[PDB]
Image (spheres, grey):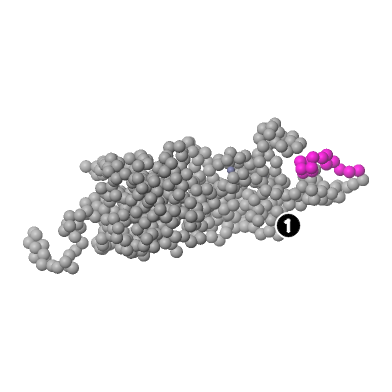
Amino acid sequence: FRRQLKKLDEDSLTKQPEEVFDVLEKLGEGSYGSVYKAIHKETGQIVAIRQVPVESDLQEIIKEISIMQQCDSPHVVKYYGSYFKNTDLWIVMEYCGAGSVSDIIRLRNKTLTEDEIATILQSTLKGLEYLHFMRKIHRDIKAGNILLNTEGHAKLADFGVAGQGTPFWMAPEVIQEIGYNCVADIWSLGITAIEMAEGKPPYADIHPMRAIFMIPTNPPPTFRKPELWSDNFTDFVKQCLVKSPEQRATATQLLQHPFVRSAKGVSILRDLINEAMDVKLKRQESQQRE
Amino acid sequence: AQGLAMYLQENGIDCPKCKFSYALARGGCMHFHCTQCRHQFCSGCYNAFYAKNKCPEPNCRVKKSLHGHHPRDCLFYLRDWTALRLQKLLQDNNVMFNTEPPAGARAVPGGGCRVIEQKEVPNGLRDEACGKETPAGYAGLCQAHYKEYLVSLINAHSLDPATLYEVEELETATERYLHVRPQPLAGEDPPAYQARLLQKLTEEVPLGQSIPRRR
Ligand SMILES: [Zn+2]
Ligand SMILES: [Zn+2]
Ligand SMILES: [Zn+2]
Ligand SMILES: [Zn+2]
């Protein structure tokens, strides 16, 4: 029985197998890797275990891990450890119950309101302020890379890895490959702000091989129907979307912008987070045969 | 991608009235309405498309309906030339061109022409690959876009198509750009007449001064 297991219980913490966590559900079978919810038995805390079965560039993953390890801030998804089980590598990291902002919009089939955007963007700007202060660049700012925990706090995840894809969020100086700095995230932030308000980035309906040429040499984008938005919102988007990087506003300056500075508390996101996670629960009841 | 289709779209179409870039090849209508500033223009020669009874140009025989004024070396005309004749103008002025795809291009064996085109779909615009047949010797492009590739080379080096014009072409060209009855002279001859007509047109009617030629 467990009499055999109890004899085996005379083992140290080093001897402990990967039973340290209890896998519960497959939250999303993402292409980067199957991602499972789990609970650490000893701490009772909920973590997310990203299985990396793919023989991807494990340097591309280790580079993502090493960037994650270098960050200690509640605005950035934390990393807890890794282990090998079966044939694949499993990566334990911070759990965000609601998911990415893109899925929140998708699940509710609903665009985010202004006040919801200002709260979500204020938290992310505090994250960008922390990273830029450390002379780091996220490099992949977008709605699908901004996770919300069950409480309602936005968190940056899935750092872009410096190469050696889709351009709609890229700054002009970064696609032209003329060299870029921290304020590159400010451009993608501005595009993300549009993506939150109207569901798609500007040039989304444009082919990538086309958009690569238009974005560097065209006026900074704006709202498709700019009569639907407040002056502070349009001005904030205008100040994020400045083609000259040296002229582009920094994350610190944007935090004092009227649109962000007056952002309401996390409590406003309460209703939409309940909406999104209810569509997730029903989505899991239909895939199971029973 | 990574083929001559990239070359076509790099230069693409830019509105002359407002400096707005579109990564769109030339084809189809070719009288282009700018979405940013509502300007009508020809995608080939960048001339204004004076549509109905508004043309300031003199001797407008075609003011009644949609028309535009195009130089002789605009794609608006050279699109009708054969692929072979265009290659002759290029060779006669010793300008190299592709007949095989560039080495980096790995054309999709099922796919055809990969030039990206905006096709009208319900409730918006959707970009799709051209996908027409890619003949051998056309450098991996379709017939329509391969000619356009050649015309860009001809426009790039400001080659004069009139160097290949026939007598009728010179008589057609003489009345269109010089507003005269081009009938021959008494005491003259058919060969000296061709060289005579060619000489004034080259000396008096310049090539398109607003065609995108990349400096
Ligand atoms: Zn225009
Ligand atoms: Zn023309
Ligand atoms: Zn006219
Ligand atoms: Zn084609």
User: Is B102 positioned to the left or the right of A107 in the image?
Assistant: right
**Which percent across, then down, holds residue A137?**
40, 59
User: Is B19 positioned to the left or the right of A35 in the image?
Assistant: right
Give the residue displayed 67% in from the left and 52% down from the top: B155
Disc 1 element: helix
What range of the chain is rendered magenta? B173-186
Q: Is residue B135 magenta?
A: no
Give the residue displayed 85% in from the left and 41% down from the top: B183
- Given the image, on which type of amino acid does mark 1 rest? Asp
Q: Is residue A229 above or below residue A139?
A: above
Q: Residues within 10 Å of mark 1 (few under 14, many from 20)?
A: few
Q: Is residue B131 above or below residue A58?
A: above
Q: Determine which quarter of the picture holds residue A161.
A: bottom left
Specify the quadrant that holds the N terminus of chain A.
Answer: bottom left
User: Is A141 positioned to the left or the right of B166 in the image?
Assistant: left
- Label 1 belongs to which residue? B92
**Which percent across, then down, holds residue A140?**
40, 55
User: Is A29 positioned to the left or the right of B201 in the image?
Assistant: left
Closest to the observer: A64 or A178?
Answer: A178
Q: Determine which quarter of the picture holds residue B100.
A: bottom right
**Which percent across, then down, holds residue A85?**
24, 61
Give the residue displayed 74% in from the left and 36% down from the top: B60
Closest to the observer: B43 or A114?
Answer: A114
Would you say residue A35 is visible in this rendering?
yes
